[PDB]
Image 1 (cartoon, rainbow, N blue to C red):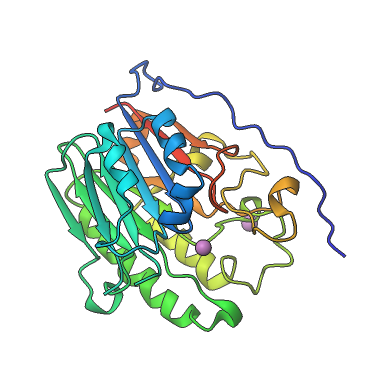
Image 2 (image 1 turned 90 degrees about the vertical axis):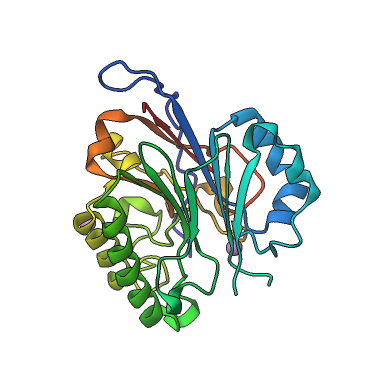
Length: 280
Ligand SMILES: [Sm+3]
Ligand SMILES: [Sm+3]
């Protein structure tokens, strides 16, 4: 039945200097934790402590802002913590930072799309950071029409932000852009995450803002690089996954891009974390 066996992928070593030789000054980690409490129970924070990022973005926290695990109070290097949950138990995002942002905002300015705690905007001196947990198209694509409306509203919102300050977007964008972004493109053409509607949406986001796919920019032809594997069917051991997590940057930030990583070995969720190195 299934045609996939193991496909090897070894993320290359961390490139910590930009094309001009400037060492990375900013390290950002993004991770769909599939439940903040479950993830922490699975020692997610031990990985964070070792990675020591300047900023940590989390998606799918599924946790009430008033029920945050006490273990989060043990992250000395990430004392500035912000969260956003649905207008409990689902969706939700978080953003933890070493340095205090100039301003933090929630949502994308559209009431219809701001009730499920999917976006946090943190403005810094030289750039604005947005982390998002994009709405899934759903089983049977029952939420694809809504997803298309979200895609348009999100694209417009981001273009607005980027028109004033360099932008960095990270998170679970719930879509594998190209065939190279998932192990089984032929069998998922009508499934959430790989529909023409979703893929065209991602392509338009890149063109309209405009934004560049950091990982693909550096590794244009590298296959089998995924960030999500279903917990079922022993998918992760066979590397039958999807690259749903990204770091999209304004073109003006490309000269500061050092590396965009996929931490394939970090356990604790059905998604692995991704890390960005910028020389700002
Ligand atoms: Sm999940
Ligand atoms: Sm293609």
